[PDB]
Picture 1 (tube, helix red, strand yellow):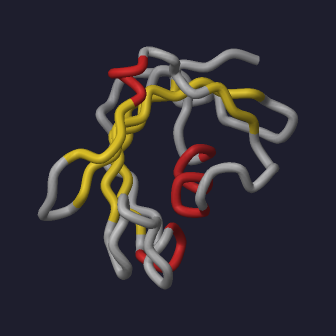
Picture 2 (cartoon, rainbow, N blue to C red):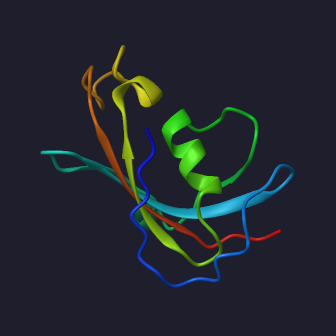
Picture 3 (cartoon, rainbow, N blue to C red):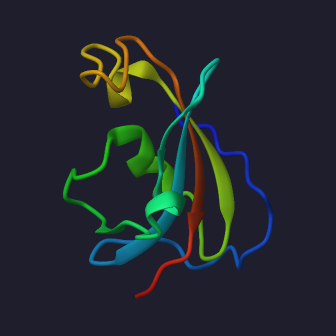
Length: 107
């Protein structure tokens, strides 16, 4: 289940497709919890492409449901990211993830 809560401004037309490499200022958040990751702190804004299963599933579907300059708000189910296993030391099992995602990409 992908639930998009858009902070408005952008263009609404530059949709992410296959064969495109995209640049995202992500910020992870635990529901009823603190932060766990920040691209803003490293200031290396996470260049990646579409269609290689590099990112998790819940983040992958929310990427194409945005456009250039937009700012959504993700809400990922446990089964699409880590909830059966839990990422060791960082994500407990059966967890619900929150992301602040802005798409400032190229191509």
